[PDB]
Length: 241
Length: 218
Ligand SMILES: *[C@@H]1O[C@H](CO)[C@@H](O[C@@H]2O[C@H](CO)[C@@H](O[C@H]3O[C@H](CO[C@H]4O[C@H](CO)[C@@H](O)[C@H](O)[C@@H]4O)[C@@H](O)[C@H](O)[C@@H]3O)[C@H](O)[C@H]2NC(C)=O)[C@H](O)[C@H]1NC(C)=O
Ligand SMILES: *[C@@H]1O[C@H](CO)[C@@H](O)[C@H](O)[C@H]1NC(C)=O
Ligand SMILES: [Ca+2]
Ligand SMILES: [Ca+2]
Ligand SMILES: [Ca+2]
Ligand SMILES: [Ca+2]
Ligand SMILES: [Ca+2]
Ligand SMILES: [Ca+2]
Image (tube, rainbow over all chains, first blue to last red; front, side):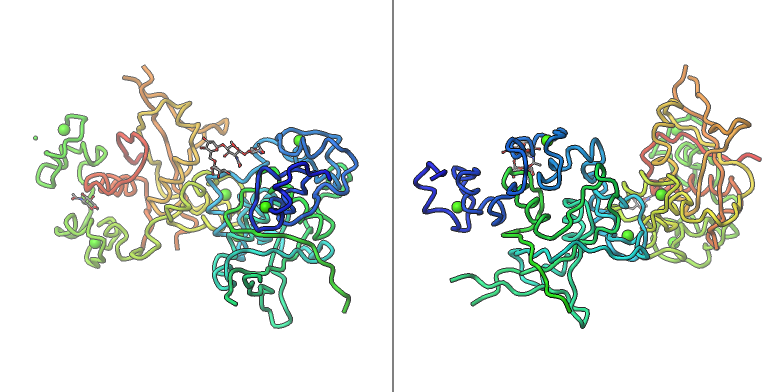
């Protein structure tokens, strides 16, 4: 039993992050603190890396994909690490409005919702990123630009709602577990069309579950800054047509 | 009630705006206006067609921009200012009320300058003034609803000269590019100076710089 605190057993999965249980040995409070991701560092080949993820400093031995790129500490420095708080509201409002805004045309601001790269062929990561957000579908879609801009900025790549055959967003109602609609189950595409080529420069997620892990890690170390009631994240495969 | 100091107690049409103190040293902004009632209709945010001529300073654009298009959205203003004339197109700032993004989006359109040069005295030393050129030019462009830029010398350097009491401010020389002005544009520098003087006279001018005076020169 890698979880030495007894009181933690009763509290894993209760839908509440319990900070006394937020450790690898306690599975990040049974996933309550890591957006349900069991172990975000499952594939990481170096044991010290989860401890160096949150330091805003490049740790080269932790910069592999499997080690979640050291929270991009080695690929983005200085002003390029965050969208300028002063420009954020503008970028959120002009995201995917069909007109190119070069000042938002960066991976840290969300690539302007691809307004500047719309003729570049889509390059989707494998699978679908599935998010549970405690906002009903109509309310969630009412601020889809802000939601997608901020989530794109966090993942430093382009995100959008996956659409069905009739052009409708794959956003489904979420019901209170064992009734009423409490939130949304959101399905997203990850478009990596603006990613870098060289092994040293590339810092995109090749599949949905990889991006989920990174988000889970941001939550585990109290670094995720996303103004939405985000409950869980995961990657799912899709069958072929 | 020529003091070189704006006194609101003396700032009235009857006293020539404190001798031009409050109208940025512009003696009479309505000098060319073919109508007498216009100074009273300039500030009402309502279209008065009889004052909508250029010489009557377009009735403060009340007939050309009355709705949401009169000012750059306060929420986006800081972004537009910082990204003005940075050589990259920002379509969200690409409007006359936001300063046309410093013409970043119209590089294929031939320059079309108004007559003369707009000369401003600003109580900021040149080095400090130049440190915020984008904000200064963007805000001034938005107000004039056209494109403004520094005049360059033979070595391509901005013509911003020290202003002495030594070094109390700057004398700035600007050009007006009307290439995107398709009546609501100023044909010459003095007209734009007059309009600015008019805004100051009626306390409508909102410009976060210690702006002393304005004038047109050929
Ligand atoms: C991983 O690194 C992060 C920094 O890169 C650490 O997050 C930062 O933590 C500090 C202190 O814990 C916090 O400072 C402010 O905290 C107080 C308010 O906290 C609330 O408000 C902020 C502002 O929106 C919010 O982000 C917090 O999550 C919380 O809701 C202030 O009263 C205090 O004076 C101080 O200014 C930073 O805000 C916070 N930064 C971010 C981006 O979250 C994080 O703690 C670390 N992980 C650890 C230590 O486990
Ligand atoms: C013109 O209108 C503005 C808008 O409130 C006002 O602040 C200003 O005092 C007015 N001008 C005069 C001369 O009253
Ligand atoms: Ca818990
Ligand atoms: Ca690090
Ligand atoms: Ca855009
Ligand atoms: Ca006076
Ligand atoms: Ca009017
Ligand atoms: Ca620009």
